[PDB]
């Protein structure tokens, strides 16, 4: 931020990222149970958009793919 004392209003994700990718991810998995979907797949699949796609993507990135409910 490099700034102190400010007045601004904006939304936030992260939690939303988890909620959106995982819901679609599960459904894509239903579509294809044998293969585990992915951010790249779901997003190509326009289930989710690169906001949802790259945001969840950096969620797995944080640990080491230890959480990614869906194959990265």
Image (cartoon, grey):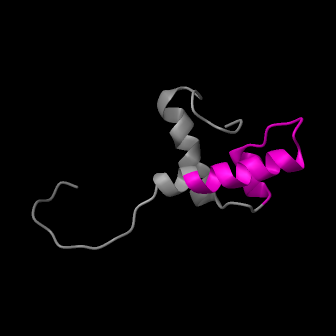
Residue drawn 57% across and 47% down? Answer: 56
Q: Is residue 42 magenta?
A: yes
**Which of 15/10 is in front?**
15
3 relative position to 15: left or right? left
Residue drawn 39% across and 68% down? Answer: 11
14 relative position to 30: left or right? left
Q: Is residue 43 magenta?
A: yes
Residue drawn 69% across and 47% down? Answer: 39
13 relative position to 72: left or right? left
Task: Give x and y (percent) for residue 13.
Answer: 45, 58
Which image quarter holds the C terminus? top right
Q: Main secondary structure of the magenta part?
A: helix
Q: Quadrant of residue 68?
A: top right
Q: Is residue 9 above or below residue 3?
A: below
Q: Is residue 27 above or below residue 69?
A: below
How many labels sit on residues?
0
Which residue occupies the extreme left position in the image?
A: 5
Task: Give x and y (percent) for residue 20.
Answer: 61, 57
Residue range corresponding to the magenta coloring: 19-45
Which image quarter holds the N terminus? bottom left
Q: Is residue 44 above or below residue 38?
A: below
Residue drawn 72% across and 48% down? Answer: 25
Q: Quadrant of residue 29?
A: top right
Task: Give x and y (percent) for residue 34.
Answer: 89, 35
């Amino acid at each position: 931020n490099l700034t102190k004392q400010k007045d601004a209003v904006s939304d936030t994700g992260t939690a939303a990222v988890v909620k959106v990718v995982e819901s679609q991810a599960e459904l894509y998995e239903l579509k294809n149970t044998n293969e585990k979907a992915s951010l790249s797949k779901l997003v190509s699949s326009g289930n989710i958009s690169q906001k949802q796609a790259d945001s969840y993507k950096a969620y797995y990135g944080k640990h080491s793919g230890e959480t990614q409910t869906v194959a990265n």
